[PDB]
Amino acid sequence: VSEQSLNGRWTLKFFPQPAVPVMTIEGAEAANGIVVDAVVPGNVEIDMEAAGLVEDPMVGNNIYKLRPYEGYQWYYSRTFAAPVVTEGQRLVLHFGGIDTFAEVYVNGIKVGSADNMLIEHDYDITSVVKEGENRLDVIIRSSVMEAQNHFLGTLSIGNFSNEESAPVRRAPSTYGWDIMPRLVSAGLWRDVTLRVENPVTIVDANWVTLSVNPKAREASESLYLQTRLPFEMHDKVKAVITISRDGRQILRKEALMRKFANLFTLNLSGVDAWWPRGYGEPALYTAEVSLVDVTSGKIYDTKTSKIGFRTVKLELDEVNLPGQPGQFQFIINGEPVFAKGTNWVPLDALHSRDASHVEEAVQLMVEMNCNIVRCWG
Amino acid sequence: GNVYEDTHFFELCDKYGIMVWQDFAMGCGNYSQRDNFAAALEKEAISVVVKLRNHPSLILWSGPNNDRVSRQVLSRVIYEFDPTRPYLPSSGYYKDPFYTENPSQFVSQIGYHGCPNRETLERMFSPDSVNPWQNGVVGMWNDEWQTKANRIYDDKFQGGRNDLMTNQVRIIFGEVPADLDDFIFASQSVQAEAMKFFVELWRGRRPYRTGIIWWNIRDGWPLLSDAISDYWGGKKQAFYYMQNVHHDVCCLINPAANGYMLKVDNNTLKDFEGVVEVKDVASGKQVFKGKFVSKANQMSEIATLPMQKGQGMLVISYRIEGNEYFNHYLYGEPPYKLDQYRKWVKKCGIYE
């Protein structure tokens, strides 16, 4: 129905982590720490430099001066107006990125516990949200100290990746590499939003290119659609599939929703294939699917994404060193492409600034004419 | 089948240079393939591996080819917590081709039964039950000797494991001695010659044979078993026989196609010179005498000895670096005369 954003100014209170880490709001407020203004999405080091508490780590040996903060806790807090929810609607609190181990409270009620900085986190706060001003509190603990909650196997010690990185789900380069500095950091480094979902909603729209014929401008595309559908809405809701490019509608298919999960296959004509750089055009088509009430015409949900009709196959060599690394070739749309490109390292040691560099960084590959890029583990 | 020994056991094995082959506490039979048993066993394996992986004496971990226990749970623990040691998923005449034609390079010898030393019998049996024959009947054991044959549940029967004793004495000596002390010496002599033959047969078949682990050196309870020493420390006749064929450099005689083969086995990394003499006990005729060169970490053929007439026993006397070591070889085919065999051991002067 809507997506209210919770980005902006938050309250950040940081303090050294005690022997028993702080998990509750009472302990976080009782702890003796410093309170400064914070920006979400952001990194805690950015908020402290804005407060004049840390020097610029990009200059000289200032990076080492952030060392004590690896054992600090970080208490994000803000208020928010609750969006309007009607009966059957669900209120979801969405985190694009929590770095890392945090307890999330809404109006003093714990709604989740995060432990992976690389994936999104969604919590159903429908039953805990209140009318009017609400409170949202996130209490992050030390990622480095979290490693001492595990016993490492022999093979996990002594590698180039830090031992602290082995038992936790974080970016290994944040602990230090030969190309990226050590800067564990913390904070809400991606968007925080409030989402309202109708009882009839799209759970997943999976687009799959079954086959492609670039010469005949044909393609067979599959849509694996999973939805949330109350049984009173079975046979009363229809799926509206729409393929278009540059405003011109290529296909509009309608089908009655009789199940919650369906597979739709579309045999398309006059459609171009997606090619990497040099081997043709990167033809993209707008693929939209909406759940519409058959009687009232109400649109309950709409999922839109730009897809490309393309097939990928990895032809492995069977003579010259069969099974050894590098003995393969990518087969795109049946053609053996020659890959030329770069390795993708972190865009910023403070990863909340990543999104601000993607445009410039991708444009480097466009000028370089890379047809491939490997996002480094 | 045993518990995991504590730290001190491995400390003594570290100190005295005794390598340790460690089984995981798994018995005869197949076990559960479900998550509950795997999780309980993974917790046990991880705990025991971290505790013992620092001892140099420990050299191997040991656990149809689809058993989750041996082929997954235990192997994953070793893979993550001890990548330095191998893991092996392994779950009546002593000259019978059953033993002498074993194809395994590394043998786990089954061991031979042997009646304990008389002092042990009088300590673990009632005065009226010290004699094995119930009502004096040669062939029957009383209810107490059947108990000390490990009868797990008090089910009254006759026969079974206890017959392994008298059968072995009958094969080697013809009849079962009615006298108790004559039976103890006879049953101990059978176990002594049988176990000595196995060690000599595997040491003499190197380099194909790579090891031998026999059952067993000590009992865990006052019992009638195939061990060579009892729970109270009573060394049986087999213990002393095995001691003389466990030397670092041992001169032994193996049966051959047309006679016997005198040989010397070296379980060290150093070469040794010596002189070996072979003589018959009763006649005293010197069968062989000459110098030998025992090359390191291998067995060496010394000489083929001519076949002797009838029964008897040979004496192997060899000196290395001014130290006289001794061994013997029982030639001929059973049954032997117990009084004659006792005369051979007495005249030889190696044992008592």
Image: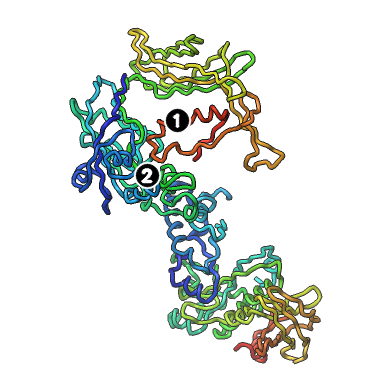
Judge left or right: residue A324 versus residue B84: right
Position of B97 relative to A317 (above/below): below
Q: Quadrant of residue B171?
A: bottom right
Q: Residue at x 52, y 83 (%)?
A: B117
The chain holding disc 1 is: A
Checking the image for residue B170, the label placed there is none
Q: Residue furthest top?
A: A295
Q: Residue at x 44, y 16 (%)?
A: A288
Q: Which mark is residue A358?
A: 1
Q: Which residue is mark 2?
A: A57
First in sequence: mark 2 vs mark 1: 2
Cα–Cα gap, marks 2 and 1? 21 Å
Total label count? 2
- Badge 2: few (under 14), some or many (20 or more) residues near its Cα, within 10 Å? some
SS at mark 2? loop
x, y (%) of residue B90?
A: 57, 58
Residue A299 lies, in percent from the top left, at 35, 13
